[PDB]
Structure formats: C-alpha cells, structure tokens
Image (spheres, coloured by chain):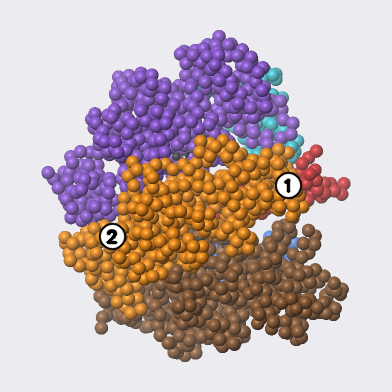
Chain colours: A red, B cyan, C orange, D blue, E purple, F brown
Amino acid sequence: ATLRELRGRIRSAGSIKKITKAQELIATSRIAKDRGLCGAYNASASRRRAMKSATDNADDLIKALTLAANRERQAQITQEISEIVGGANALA
Amino acid sequence: PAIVGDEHYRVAQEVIRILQRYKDLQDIIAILGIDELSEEDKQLVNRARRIERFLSQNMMAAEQFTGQPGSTVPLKETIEAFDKLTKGEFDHLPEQAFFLIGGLDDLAKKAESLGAKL
Amino acid sequence: TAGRVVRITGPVVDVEFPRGSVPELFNALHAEITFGALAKTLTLEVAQHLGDSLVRCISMQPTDGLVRGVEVTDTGASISVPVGDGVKGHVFNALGDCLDDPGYGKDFEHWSIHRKPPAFSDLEPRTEMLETGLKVVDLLTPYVRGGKIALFGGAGVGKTVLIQEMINRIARNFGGTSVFAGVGERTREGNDLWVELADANVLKDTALVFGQMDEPPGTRMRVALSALTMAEFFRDEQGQDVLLFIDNIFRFTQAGSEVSTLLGRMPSAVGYQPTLADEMGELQERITSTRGRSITSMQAVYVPADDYTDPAPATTFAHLDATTELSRAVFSKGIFPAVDPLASSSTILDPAIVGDEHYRVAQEVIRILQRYKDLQDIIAILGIDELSEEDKQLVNRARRIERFLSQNMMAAEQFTGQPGSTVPLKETIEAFDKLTKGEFDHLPEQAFFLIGGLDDLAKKAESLGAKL
Amino acid sequence: EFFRDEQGQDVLLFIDNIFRFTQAGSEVSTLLGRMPSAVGYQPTLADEMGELQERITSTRGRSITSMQAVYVPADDYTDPAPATTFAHLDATTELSRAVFSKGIFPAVDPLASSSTILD
Amino acid sequence: EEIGTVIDAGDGIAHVEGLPSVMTQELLEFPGGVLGVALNLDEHSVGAVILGEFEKIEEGQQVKRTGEVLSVPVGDAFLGRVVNPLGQPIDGQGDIAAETRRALELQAPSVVQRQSVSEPLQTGIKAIDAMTPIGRGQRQLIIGDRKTGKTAVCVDTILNQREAWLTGDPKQQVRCVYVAIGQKGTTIASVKRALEEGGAMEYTTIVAAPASDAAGFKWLAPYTGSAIGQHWMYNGKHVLIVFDDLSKQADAYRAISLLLRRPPGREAFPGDVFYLHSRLLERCAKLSDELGGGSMTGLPIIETKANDISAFIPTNVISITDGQCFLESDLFNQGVRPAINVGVSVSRVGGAAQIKAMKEVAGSLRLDLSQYRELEAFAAFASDLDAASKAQLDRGARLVELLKQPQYSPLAVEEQVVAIFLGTQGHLDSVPVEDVQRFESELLEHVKASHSDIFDGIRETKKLSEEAEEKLVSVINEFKKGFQAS
Amino acid sequence: EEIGTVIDAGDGIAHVEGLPSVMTQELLEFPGGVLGVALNLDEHSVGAVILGEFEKIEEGQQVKRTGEVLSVPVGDAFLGRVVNPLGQPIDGQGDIAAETRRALELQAPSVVQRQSVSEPLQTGIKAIDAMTPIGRGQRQLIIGDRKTGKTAVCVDTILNQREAWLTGDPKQQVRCVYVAIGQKGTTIASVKRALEEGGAMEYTTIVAAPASDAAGFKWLAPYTGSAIGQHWMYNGKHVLIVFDDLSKQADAYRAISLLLRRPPGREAFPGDVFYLHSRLLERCAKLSDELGGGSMTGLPIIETKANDISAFIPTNVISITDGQCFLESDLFNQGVRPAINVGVSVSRVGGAAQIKAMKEVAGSLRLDLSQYRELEAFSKAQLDRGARLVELLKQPQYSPLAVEEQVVAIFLGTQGHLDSVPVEDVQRFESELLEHVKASHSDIFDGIRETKKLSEEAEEKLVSVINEFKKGFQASDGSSVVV
Ligand SMILES: Nc1ncnc2c1ncn2[C@@H]1O[C@H](COP(=O)(O)OP(=O)(O)OP(=O)(O)O)[C@@H](O)[C@H]1O
Ligand SMILES: Nc1ncnc2c1ncn2[C@@H]1O[C@H](COP(=O)(O)OP(=O)(O)OP(=O)(O)O)[C@@H](O)[C@H]1O
Ligand SMILES: Nc1ncnc2c1ncn2[C@@H]1O[C@H](COP(=O)(O)OP(=O)(O)OP(=O)(O)O)[C@@H](O)[C@H]1O
Ligand SMILES: [Mg+2]
Ligand SMILES: [Mg+2]
Ligand SMILES: [Mg+2]
C-alpha cells in the first residue's frame, strides 16, 4: 500500500501545482488590472508571490514523492523476485 | 442504452461524471479549501456530495447493524430521483438528508425532520 | 577422539568425529592454522549436528589458511569467559582474553557464555524512574532503573553520543559495576571509550568487552553473550547493581543473519535468519533484573537504511521498557538529541508512576507535537499563513517546544565546545507546562535551542533581544 | 574496431537501443538460471555494460564515437539499467517535439541537453 | 516400545529415523525429559520440532513414541496459574490437578453445533461496547502499531469480568485465558500483577511462551490456551481468550517451517499460515443449547508496522475475525484514548451483542462518527458552513470527547448507557467540548449518589423504560443548573 | 606436487577437484596465468572465484597451488606504479621489485593498538580543511551523486601531499594509494595524468579494476590497495588511501554472491556486504606509538542515486566511517564547486586534528554558513557576508592550497575584509591577494606554518597588507574595494 499511497500523493500534488500555477498567473494579470492565499500579507502581488512559492513547493514535493515512489517500485520488484526465487530454490 | 434505455443510461453517465469530477477536486478542496473552486465547481461539489450520500441506502440485512429497517426503491424512482439530483433540484436540502434513506419520500421526510423542505 | 575438518565455507567449518565422540551443541573445539602470517588457534563453536557424526561449527576467528583434514580437538565445554571483580578495569575480547594485559584473568573463575535466562518466578517488573537530566528523556521517555532502555537510530543520528551521554550521567556517580559491550562497532570508538573512562576514573568500575566490525560473524554474534555473562555474574553472585551498555545489538542480529546464511538455513524475510526472533529473545531475556538484583541495560539499536520496519529493530522493540527512537528528520533540524518525541515510549510514563502533573504535561506536549505533525502536509505547500488562528498559535508553540526538547549534552562538548547542562525533572515539568500554556510564546524560537532549564532560556532570550 | 585499428579511420557507432542490450543480457541471465540482482537485472549488469562501453574509446590517434539511444524504464533515471548506462555517457542530446514544431532543425532541446566537457 | 534415533539436529529441529508407527503430530520423547512433535513424515525420517531445550539433543540419541497426538491437561485447577504451552506450571506454585486431557487439534464446532452470538461481553470501554460491541462466542481482533493500547484493552476487558465472577452464576461468569506469545518475561509478570490487583487471577489463566522460549512453544501457546478454554466452553461455561499476540506466533511458525525446509510463500511465511490462524480462531464459538450453551470469545492481537494493515498476517487475521478494533498512534497522541479508528473498526455481530438500552442509545453512533470525521476533513478550510454542517461538527466533537476513557477505568453497562444517552440524545450540546468529559463524570456520579434507580432499571431490565428516560432527562436538566462550565 | 583439475566452470566461478592440502582463501593458478581464490572447500571439490579472465578457464584444465593465502606483493617499489588487484603492473613499465608479500585479510589493529587521531591530513580544499577537517588515521566518506566532483576532491587531496613529500621526513610524508574500482579506463588515465603533472606519482600507487574488469577484480581491488598501504602504515609511515568507489565494489561482491547462489537481502545485496566494507575500513587506523605510530587515512567514495543518502550501501558506509563530505548535485550545477553541503557534512574525529590558526578562523565560518543557508532560503548584512563566504569556499580543480594560505583566505572571509569587495570578484581578489603575500610579506605564511598559530603581530601585519592591497585592487565593475 506504500506505492499506492505515494502515487495518490503524487496525483494530489500535481493537481495542487496546476492550481497554484494558474492562480499565480491570474494574480500576475490582476496586478496590472477576503481570500487567504496571499501569504503573510494579512499577518494581488502578495498572492502572486505566495502562489509562486506554493507552486514551487508543490513541484519540490512532486519530485521527492516521485523519488520515493521509484524506490518503492524497485524495492517491490526486488522483493517479489526474492520470494519467487526463494520458493524455487526451496523446491530445487 | 440498448438494454437499460436512454434515460437510465444518461442519468447513470451523468452521476458517474459528477462523481469523477468530485474525486478530481477532492485534493484541491483538502489543501486550498472549497472557496478557491469556481462557482460551477462548487455547484458540482455540492451536487456530488448529495449524490454520493443518496447512493447509500438502508438495507434490510443491515438492520442489525443500524437499528433501522431497510428500504426498497423501484428502478423508475431511482432514475427519476438521480436525474433530479444531477440537475440540482435538491441542492437546497442539507447533505445529511440524503444519508441512509430509500426513495424521494424518505428524502422529504428526513429533510423535514432536519428543518428543510422538499 | 579427535575430529577432522571436512568442509570450510568462510567462517563455518564442518568437522567429522568418530562415532560416539560427536561434541555437544555449543561446545568449543580447537583447530590450528599453521600458515606463517595467519598462524593461529581457531576456536570453533558447535552449531549443528549434521548426522553421520559430522558437526557444523562457527569459527570465532577468520578461517583463512585452514586446511581440510586438520585435527580438531573438542574441549568438552562451551566458550567460557573469566568472571569476578578482577574483570573490572580491563578490556576483553569475546573469548575472554584480556587485551590490555594479555594472560590476565586466566586464573579467574570462568563461566560458560551460554546459560538459561532467569526463571519466570524470579522476574519482577521494574517501575522506578532513572532520572538523567535530559529534558526529552525525563519528560517523554523516562528511563527505568533496573529496566531495559534502547536507543534506535539510522546511521549517524547520535546513538553512540547518547550512549556516552548516559555513561556520563548514570555510570560516573554509579555505585555498582558497569559492563560495556562493543558489538560490531568501530574499533577506534572502543579505544576512545577506553581512554575516556580511564580519564574520568570510571574504568576501575567497568569491564569492557569488544568484538568490533573487523571480526568474523561468529565473534560478533557471541561477544554480547560474553559481556552479558560478566554482567550476570555481577548480578547474581556479587549482589551488585549493574549497568550494561551495548553498542550495537543490531550488529548481533546482523552477524546472526550472516552466520545463518553460511549455515545453509533457508532465509526468512529480507534475507534474515529464520531464528531471528528466537536468537534475540534468548539474548534479551538474559539481560534483565530479577527480584532484588538489578541490571539497568542501555542498548543502541541500529536501524538499517532508516527503515524502522526492518525485521531486526522491529523484533527488538518488544524487549524494552523504554525506547528512545532517534530520527533523521529531527537530526536534520539540528535538534540534539535527535529524539522523535512521538515515536519514543516508556512503560512508566503513566500517572500511576510519575504522577498527575508529569503525565499531564507530557501528554499535552505530545498532543501539540502530534497536531503540528498532522499539519505538515499543508505547511509544506502553503506555510502557516493559511492556518486558523488556533492552529497558527499551536504551530508557533510546537516549534518552540520541539526546539526546547533539544539540549546541550555533556558528550556534545567535544563537537561544539559548549559544556552540557543538567535539568532537574521538576524544572523540566514546570518549564514545559509554561511552554504548552503559551507563557514563552513571545520569545524567539532560537532562544529555546540547545539549552538547559529556564535560567538558560532567560539568558539566551536576553542575548537575542527578548526577555523572560 | 576494425575500422579504427586496422584502417586508421574515425568511426561513428550508433546503438539503438542500448537498453535492449541490457535487457537481452537480463533475459539470457534468467534463461541460464542465474539469480536476478536488484530490480531483476542480471548480477553482471555493470560488468557487461563496461565490457561493451570501454571498447568505445579513442586510441592511437583514432576514435570510435558512439551515439546511443537510451530507454529509461518508468522514466526512473535511478533504475539500474539507465544508471549503469549513464555511468559511461559523456553527453546527452534530447530532441524536442516543441523545437521541431517550430521548424527548428535539428530539434535539439538546448536546455534539456547537456555535455560533460562544457567546462 | 517403538524407538527411533536422532540422525541430525539443530536450531530446535531434529530428524529421527525409525518410529515406523509414529503419527502425524505425535508427541515424541527425547532423552532428558525433552519433548518434540512429528511434523514431517517421509520414508527416510521424521522431522520433529523440539518443544523445550534442544541444546541437549544429540545425534544418536534414542527417541520414543508417546502414542499421543499433541494434548494438554485441562481443568479448573488452571485458574490463577501461569503455565507453559504444555500446561506445566511456571509460576513456582506446584502441580496443577488436571481434570482431564484435551488434544490440541480437536475440531471446531460445526455449523449445526452453534447458535447465534446474542450475549454481550462487556469490556467496560465505552467506545467498544457502544460502537464495536463484542458478544459471547465472537472473535474481535485488536490490531494496531506498537504502544497503541492493545494489551490495555484486552486486560481491561479481563478485569471488567470481576463482577460477573463474583455473582457466582456460571451463565454470567467469564473465565479468562491470557496467552502471552513472544513477550518479555517481565512484561508477562506486569500483566499478571495488573490482573492480581484487580482480582482477575481468581478466574484467569495465563499460558506463557516468552521470547526466550523455543519457536515450538511460541507456535503452540495459542492452541494450548484454546484447548484449556475449550474444556470449559464445552462444559457450559463462558470463556474469554486473549492472544497477545498472533503476529509472533506466525513468526515462530515461519521459523519452524523454514528450519524444516518447507517451501516459503509470501514474506517467507509457509503456505498454511492463514490455516494456522483460521483453525485456531474458529474454535472460538457460541455453542448451541444442545451442547450446553457455552462459549469462547476470542480477542486476538495483531501488531502492525508503520500502520500497514496490508501486510500478510494482518490481512489474514482481519479476514478471519468477527470485526476489529483498529488502534492508531496518531489518534492516541491526539488524546483519543482508546485510540480506536471509528471509520474502519467494526463488529460483525452488531446490535445482537448489546443489551436493548445500549442498542437504542448507540444505534447509529458508529456511522455518525464516520460521517463526522469525513465532514471534519472536508470542512477543514470552509468559511461560513451550513447550519446543519456546523451542528454536525459540534455534535461529533462532543461524541468524540464522550468516547474518551482512561486506562483501568471501566464503566458498568448502565453507566455506559447513560453516558452515551447524554451525547446521542443531544444533552451535551449545551456543554463546551472541553468540559464534556468532566460533565459526564459528574453526571454519572450524581445519578450514582441519587436517582440510582435509573441504573438499577437499566441493569435489571436491560432496557431504558420510557419513564426512566423521562426521569433521566429531568435529572440531567436539573444537574446542568449546578454544573460549572469552566 | 598437488595438481587439481577443473570439473566445471561458469560465470567467474570454477570448481576444482583434488588439491587435498589447499588452504582456505589460497590463490590457485589456472593455465594461462589465470588466478583464483579458494572460497569453498568441501570433500568433493574446491569452489574458486576467478580473479582475471574467466573465459580462459576450461573443464579438465590443471590447477596448481601457490602455497600462499590470498595476498599481494608489497614494498616501496609500488610508488609511482599502476597495478591490478593482484599487484601485477599494468602501466607497461616493467617488473615491480616487491619487498615481501602481505595477506589481504589480516585483522585490523585492536582497541589497545591504536591512539587518538591528532595530526591533520591537509586536503588543500578550503571547505573540507575548514569545516570537516581530516586527521591522519581517520576514515572520511566522500558521498554524492554521479558527476558531483568526488574524484576531484580525492585527487586534489593527493596532490596536496607534494609539499609534505618533498621534506623527506617520514613523519610528515604521506604515501598515497588510489584504488579505482569499476571506473572507466579513460578516467583512470586522466587521474594518473593529473597526478603526474602535479608531481604526485612520486608518492602514489594506483590499483586499477576498471569498468571492463570482471567482478572478482572489482571486489578484490580495495583489499589490494589496503594491503599495500598497510605494509607502509605498520612501518611507521603515514598513508592515504582513496577507494573510488565502494558502490561499485559492493555491486561486484553482490554479483559474485548471486553467482554463488547465496540468498540476498536488501537491494539484493548479500547479508555480509556490510562486513565487506567494514573490515576494509577498519584497517585504516592511527597506530599506537608502540606499533610505530603509522597511520592510514581512508577516503572511501560512495555514489548515491538522486542524492538519497538513506539507501542501504550509503548508510552502511556512513555507519562505518568517521564523518562524511556530502557533495550535492544542486550546488554543483549552481557552480558551487567543490559542492560540499554544510548541513550534512561533518568530521566526527577531525576536530582535534586541526591546527590552531585554522580552528580560530573557521569556528565561526561553520556557523555563519549554516545559518546563512536557511536565511537565504527565505540580516541583509549577514546575507552579504554569507554570499562572500560561499564565494570564498569555491575553489578551482587541481589547485590545493597550503594550510597557511587557507588560514589567510578564511581570515579574509571571516574578518569582514570581503564585505567591501564585490561578490563576483571575491575569488579573484583572494587569489591575487594570496599571490601578493607570497611575493612580499611571505614571512606571514612562514610564521603560521612554523607556529601553527596566528599571532597578534602577524594578524596586525596581515590586516595592514590587506588594506594596502585593497588600495590598488581593480574590481571587475571598476569600483575601488577600499574600506
Ligand atoms: N549532541 C550532539 N551535539 C552535536 N553533534 C552531535 C551530537 N550527537 C551527535 N552529533 C554528531 O553526530 C555524529 C554522529 O553521532 P554518533 O556517533 O553518536 O552516531 P550514531 O548513531 O552512533 O552513528 P553510527 O550509525 O555511524 O554508529 C557525531 O559525530 C557528531 O558529529
Ligand atoms: N485508555 C488509555 N488511556 C491512557 N493511556 C493508555 C490507555 N490505554 C493504554 N494506555 C497506555 O498506553 C501505553 C501502551 O499501552 P499497551 O501496553 O496496552 O499497548 P500495546 O499496543 O499492547 O503495546 P506493546 O507494543 O508494548 O505491546 C501504556 O503506557 C498504557 O498505559
Ligand atoms: N573544484 C572544481 N571546480 C570546477 N570544476 C570542477 C571541480 N571539481 C570538478 N569539476 C568539474 O566537474 C567534473 C566532474 O567532477 P568529477 O569527475 O570529480 O566527479 P565525480 O563525482 O567523481 O564523477 P563521476 O560520477 O564521473 O565519477 C570534472 O570533470 C570537472 O569538469
Ligand atoms: Mg555509533
Ligand atoms: Mg501489548
Ligand atoms: Mg569519479
């Protein structure tokens, strides 16, 4: 279930990255021209910077998750082979 | 369509489309919240939550697990009810009205018990 | 009545004996390697009876140079090590040979390194706090006097430094005897420990047994039993309070896996020996207090490839009273000791043993850190700005708490030049009560890093610009 | 090698696809009953790749230069086959659909492509 | 008598030649009092697992048949005793006067030898008794990571049977068997002390196979405990058996099977590990009235790693038992204790394992909490939710508070009925979330001090009468005036 | 004499019947000068791992004893030579007149045969020599992704020992062994060329098991280099051994184990791959004075995949060595070279083996850089200082610095003398300035080198010279860098 979970996380992170990127570009448009995606502004330009940061973080997260997923993929192949060959060796 | 007919098939496909879109949106709703969705996507999310709840049903064999006697919904009532649900005709009812009931009469009764009216 | 070598497969040797003279399991046999540079007397330990009067044995020394057909003599007994007050202050190898004074101890009483664990009716659960002065240990993972403590961690997250810390905090003013087992660890670490103990005047109360990385798997599997035999003698015969330090018990399991492979056994999961749990259980159940006879054991458990689900540490968990799980993620943040406060545990962290206040404060710390961990997915993308005011407040509190669980350690001075600190348990409880209640929320986060008690907190907050 | 060593020529050796060489080696290893290594590749993966690649060299003033199509399983560059191959690679040329669709030939992606001697 | 000879031996396994008439799974005597069991029978030899200390086994030693399949002594004398998987005392209190002997592999009751599970086995834990109720004859898996509270749930269930024991009525009494498999000896001793303080050792037996035991003893201990329980079950008694835990028994069986060189399966487990657990757990049953009406309730424990219930052994055992209580570290650390994951924890007997009053108050509690958790996740970043959604969230937070319970703090079933009634009928809505616990604690105390007839009515009639409901509602409303909401 | 015969041969393994008197791990000669090591000895045959050209082995071939356990020739004649893991020359320069032979699997010095690491082993790399100092007898892991500069660090360290060599004092000289395991032949040739141009082959031996070699040679190479080095170390010499890289040796050993049908574990590695690396690296030690005080410093190299230091082999080696220099690909591609990562890079035991001047100038440097990284992730003055420090730690390949020059450069960075200088010129600035101090005021370097300390008078003169240099330093931008 580790690989299934990692794939689900990768899908979620991809959707988030797409949304944040669209928000960043729309905030760029609205700069030339309530909500909480403005970063530390409460604590358009600020939303643009916050969405840039968020989409970059989503990209970093996708890369890390993909690395972990590929490690799990390789480990699963190796383990499955180990079980198959262990059984075959037992019978041989 | 050849077997179940055009109405059944179209309603089924619409339900599936809505639920698929809702599943696509769930991650965004979880991280960024629902207010960041488009108004059309918010409409779809409300419809989808009501639809998924209305797919649940009080089954007879489940009385022992819920204390509630089961129900049976004729095919025609199912098709008409889900046609209405996909069109947004029950969007004014709380989603909890759609949980573990039978047909539209049960829906009206549960909505009344929760304050709203069908 | 002598046998002869018939097979050699690395550190494992098959020996044929005349019918009727087959040695008993665990008997020590002796063979000779005569090749000049590698000349030595091999100690073999009987591991299996193969049938037809053949035994499979594990060599305690490398078998390089051994020849098929050479004579093998059965000593008639298992490997035995010298016991008594004389072993204190001296360094030994897994066979009981003194390394700092060769020949020393040959005249002492010798005990077989193989014995049964104490009878179940002699066992008494230990619930008594061993106070360390480390904030995180005392608060969240209180150690048990006469109990079993483990330090889990991946490569280089601070296990050995924490073992040295606990030697400093527990062994130095200890009144009883200490036994240190180096199992499959760095030889220079052993030399460093020897020198450090001599400097601190603790060596005279300590027996050091080393079988380190550059040893055959058989020595790495038996050295722990040798050290444990000395500890058992001190516990049972001498009626002494005993400390037992082991670094690293995972190396014992790993050597068992290597030996099992050589012995021809079918592998279990992840290539481990089928008897992994059973070997570990024999060893661990020997390491224990009995009624009126106390051993406090502290063991470092290596976690392969940072995989806490690996069968070796996973099996080790059940044998412990307190478990400090070091985390790579904590280590990466500069937090020393790199304790994972959410994964560590103590069987005595409950209100009945530590009291209502300690338990409540520990539980509130754990709740806040758990909430912070749950928010990490959201924070990793958006930061804290999207959180609700309650969650923002909690996240600020949790960051300060996780920093304040760090501590300048005594053994860390060699790395940072900063002397360590000791925090009384009462002060730790009070300080974390204030922290969870939000009384230090105005102080900057860095003020909580690598300090001791509240006085240090005030001084560092002042040095930064705030004021407590 | 005959062209380089006996005719004293410079040779361009194209290999499409080097991954299929690695995989054929894995299949042969399986047929011969050898226990698979990590991710199911032959235990001698690196040795086979080295024996092939170390023969592609410059010597005595003449060279064999090789352009090799590489398939990356699962797009995973840490997969043993692409990792072993890239242990021997000196440059990468990625041809991009985007660049081709602009009429730019050769359709080399100037940002994706790289070379180990551009220093 | 027939005699074989040891031809090879190691690691707790032996191979014996001869013994032509040995049976599969027969007990074999080795010299020195050591016993074994014949697992592999082929023309050449018998593969035997040594149940004890194998370091004394040598090539050439004589092995004797016993003529007995694996069996253990059984009787009432095992109550209050600690034994090893052969039924031999290990508590140092002398011999146990066995009533008789039971073969370990006697078959489970058939489909027609049982009747439906219909009697509650109260745990004293509100979350379990209201949301995953356990009946008599049920198998309820307690599964979770280390230190999530699995042993605490099982031991508190054992301790909660003391009142039933004191009644003296065997139709009410529950005798308890605690099987410790692969546990450190001091942990078993601490469990025994906990039982002793609560007076549970009067009706409890501990079968102990600590981590120092041979893999054979660890493999057998569940079956030994099951046979001891079955002796009572078939004599009209009610038995609760705890297996702490079956993960270690599966590992011990795998060790034995690999040492015998049987071909491994997934995770190197033998092909019949599922069978190992299923044939054990199907012996827990509710017997029909023709066979005495006895029952044995099973509480197997499974330890998962990294909250991975998809591993081989957890999946097997989940697919065997009549529901599971899933304990989570994240829930535990949040303060949800017992740390039950409500969405995925289920009881497959359901309301049949509850008294009427509990069934009525706790009707849809589990689904309500599941939907609450779903809504909580969905409404995490919602601003200005619906009125109905806000009401659902408030109610669910109150219910979650209501289901928190300290260790060693059992509630009688009537107290649980009243506590649940408070939450599900809406009487906690006016109470702040943070005070919910306190409120319940004080309300129950109040009903205990006066209006104690509400508890009496629930206890004696198993249902909350309409008039008792009216009185309880009035009592709650009156108590709320004096309650100080911090 | 005893003659065995090949009964079967496959995939670098052979089985030989006969040779009743053969020893475990004995070297066996197969026809055509092929060698094998007797791994498994039973009553039917001897399993042998072939070290060399396995394709020449045939059934029925005669096999002869060597009478020698697995061993290599050792002696001073190996300096400046390139050999294979058997000690056979491969540089085409004739025979190597060996002093003696040394068995490959001799045990490491015991806990009581060592002493604390106390003498620095200067690498000439400012980042390492300042932040992860290496003492003689220490094992420092060089770990990173492919093409992150690992070989460059190790080769620069070897090149840095030329000045020590020229003194002729065996207490100061460092003899170098460079073991190439599974490396491309062209890269070994380039390494040898760089060592020759730097005058380093005089005191360096190369053990080569290139990528084209069979697994037996790749598996053996580190032990051969270690034995060559140990011969010198036990004779009171100081040795530096580089294993480039141990990832490939682990792969070779895994191949050999699988071909022997040993059941694997994690990542299909044999259960004793940890032992493979740990017994090798335990033999790098600082000997006690009773044993001569010699030392062997190990620089194992590990290649990670995608910067994953939590994998099996990297974690094994991390748990063997006394610290690691983590080379990050992100830094390398940003032009930060050598691409050392401060957060993960640490010297466990080299803190004591650091001259006093370097300690004084670098103790702050460590903290400044560690905190500047987190700040830059997101004061302004500390940002400028951190940029200047990151610039200062950059270093060209093949150009190690003497410790006195490192002290002066770290002084410049740490004492704020670069706050005025433009970032883009810091490098050039430092270079020119150091050259100035060599041409004139060279007594500063002499004082530091003799005393190993930075004196108050020398510090004052250094500041004066820095100001005078700033007077006439032409920034690329054109602006003066004065004050
Ligand atoms: N309290 C501390 N303060 C500062 N640095 C520390 C501290 N603890 C550990 N370190 C750093 O971490 C390094 C590793 O510590 P330690 O040797 O205890 O790790 P380990 O877990 O035993 O490692 P291994 O798996 O390699 O044996 C130490 O050399 C030191 O650099
Ligand atoms: N309801 C509870 N409230 C508070 N603490 C509890 C509760 N239940 C258990 N605990 C505590 O949680 C810790 C773990 O409990 P327990 O030993 O029962 O868990 P486990 O899953 O069986 O553990 P292990 O992995 O050691 O076998 C113990 O300290 C116990 O006191
Ligand atoms: N200090 C440096 N300054 C500038 N360029 C450098 C430096 N070190 C290395 N390089 C460049 O980086 C290239 C790769 O470095 P190097 O070969 O040392 O890395 P590596 O990690 O050992 O590589 P590989 O994976 O090929 O073995 C070198 O060819 C050189 O071009
Ligand atoms: Mg360590
Ligand atoms: Mg438990
Ligand atoms: Mg390199």
Q: Depth check: give the residue in front, E405 or D87.
A: E405
Instruction: Report x, y in % for residue F108.
Output: 43, 72
Sequence-earlier tag: 1 or 2 = 2
Which numbered tag is attached to residue C468?
A: 1
Q: Position of residue E387 (x, y in %)?
A: 71, 25
Q: Which chain contains the residue that carries disc 2?
A: C
Under mark 1, the amino acid is Leu
SS of the residue under disc 1: loop
Front position in the image: C287 or E269: C287
State the residue at coordinates (71%, 77%): F455
> Residue F220's image quarter?
bottom left
Q: Seen in the image, is A77 located left or right of residue D68?
A: left
Q: Residue at x 29, y 23 (%)?
A: E235
Disc marking residue C78: 2
Residue E399 seen: no
Q: Quadrant of ligand 1?
A: bottom right
In the rendered image, which quarter is residue E73 located in? Answer: top left
Q: Is residue F292 above or below residue D68?
A: below
Foreground mark, 1 or 2, reads 1
Where residue F412 appears, as percent x and y from the top left, is: 75, 73
CA gap, disc 1 to disc 2?
64 Å
Q: Secondary structure at mark 2?
A: strand
